[PDB]
Amino acid sequence: GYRKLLDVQIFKDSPVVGWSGSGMGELETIGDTLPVDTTVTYNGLPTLRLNVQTTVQSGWWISLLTLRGWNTHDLSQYVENGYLEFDIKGKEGGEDFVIGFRDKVYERVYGLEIDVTTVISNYVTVTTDWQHVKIPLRDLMKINNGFDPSSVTCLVFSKRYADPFTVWFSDIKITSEDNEKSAPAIKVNQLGFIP
Amino acid sequence: LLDVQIFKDSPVVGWSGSGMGELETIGDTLPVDTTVTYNGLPTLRLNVQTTVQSGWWISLLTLRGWNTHDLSQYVENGYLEFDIKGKEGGEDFVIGFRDKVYERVYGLEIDVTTVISNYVTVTTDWQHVKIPLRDLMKINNGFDPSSVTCLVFSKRYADPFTVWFSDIKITSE
Image 1 (cartoon, rainbow over the protein chains, first blue to last red):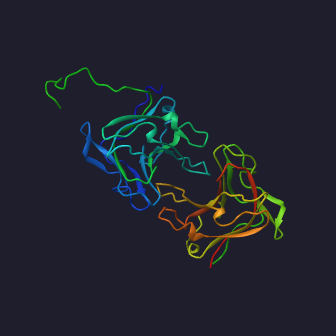
Image 2: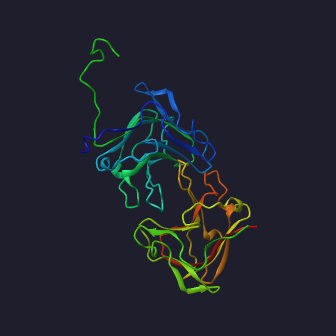
Image 3: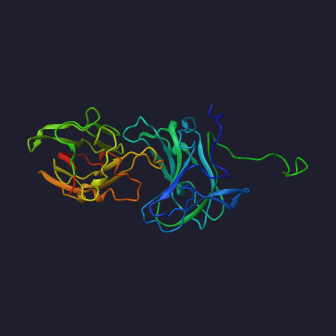
């Protein structure tokens, strides 16, 4: 029945509601969230820019991208076969940082919010060219330490090393099963005209 | 400034626990030891009973039964004081404070912490240790000292150990 689950789109073409910041303003932000790059594009669509401009020695920087404008979202049924997919490319290459999810459970008094994380390098080796990466949910959200996949609020990016860096994201979303995207068996001028 | 007594002679409302029950608790809070006394009063026993590999053990001691407490005027010259002594010695763990701010979306609760080894070397005899609040609550973290809810004790190493606290409180000038 997870196969009838629709994709959960986190970023497509516009500013995402959430909060991004750092101790000394190392992380580039606007309106306290990630800026949308209209110059570096993918498939003609704008990208999401994660830009740590100076060496990070405030100790930290974080980026929270909400799935439902801060409300919780039930993702339990995406865990056993789903993935976190997105395309990325670095300014140079070899960029690395923490990536995961955060939940919210008001009834867990010893910690209202818990995060599950991993390093992006474990699933890709960022280059200067676009790459499509798939992180598997079951690899993150396989608890025992409190995380509640039925109460997820945000996706998270976070400091790994203090090195400054820049990457661009595209088509960030949550899938329930596994795919190989595709395209019609068509011409660009199916339809006679081209939209 | 008025003192903010955290522990004196009775169970503290809060939540203490661990991934697999390594931390000795009762009613999900730290046991009050009545055989180990000091200055006539009972003591608070923090006891992880086995090499802990849940990943974690934590103790939240509320200052106001979960309500936030205003400790802003205490940051400058305030201290967190208490007396301590261990079962074997050299015991070390994380100690700090946790706040609660519902409208701060990037983190409803934030912890400001340090390790006791930075302030004292636990011996098998009573010892008094004063940690300046300025050493913890002075950050561009978003941590709000006027919204503090709990004192925190948490895992540092997976090694089991036992310590007793006494007269835990917050004092100023």
